[PDB]
Length: 240
Ligand code: NA
Image 1 (cartoon, rainbow, N blue to C red):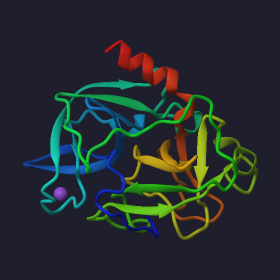
Image 2 (image 1 turned 90 degrees about the horizontal axis):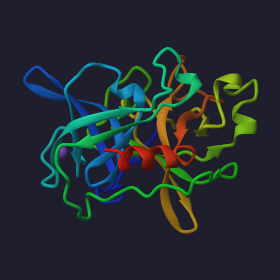
Image 3 (image 1 turned 90 degrees about the vertical axis):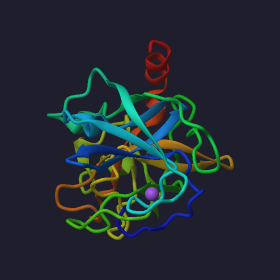
């Protein structure tokens, strides 16, 4: 997250860190959202590589013991069947991870609530992106979980020529684009939390930013629109 602030450690208890085994250690690669005690929602592109993955819930500082973490292996990966790694702009950038164990819920570990199917945010709706991704274009991962306020940019604007044009689809949500605050590498897969009727819900799964940089004016961060995938999510969970 470029232009973020440190999150309070109990603000975003559905946020997870998706990590891969790297030699004798683990490395953060993506975010995700805990949606059941044994299921995480992330981006498909985050699990393209043939790596050994784990999820960390209750994480705040990637580099220090928080005293709240639970570490769990990923047992099964279900990528959306229409995902094409050659074509992030086509959409379908969503995957579900079944965890090897069910995590225990507490103030640091909670299920993300998802929007009702079909919900579309009004332009300029209030949302926060969260994650441990790069804090500058071509920078380094955050240590501590970051948040940035990224109001939505509706489809009509986002898909206009000076924004993303044809690359953004109605199955996506755009947010930000002010040139200061954005998602960045390492935030992919994590949530966009939007305040609706008094309650934050996870409306987006971070999918992509510009190839020209993270915080680029009129290139808002692009998210998979969770409300387009409710039936898919429920079908996967019911059949696994
Ligand atoms: Na930690």
